[PDB]
Length: 59
Image (spheres, rainbow, N blue to C red):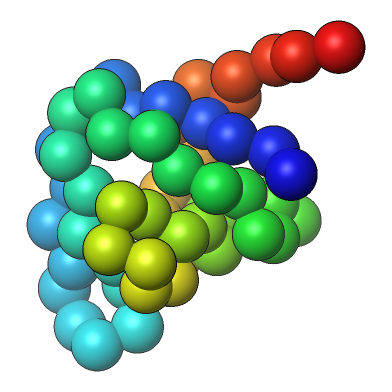
């Protein structure tokens, strides 16, 4: 598993995007595009722009 942390808030504009709050931690499910599919605190999943995120690293 991979995780990223949000530096900013993000508000979903339609059913497919996913809302996030500053400092939220997210599980990166698909990082292949400009918008990553992530799973947030609610367990739901959706796309969020990656530029608001910082990938978190671990050995």
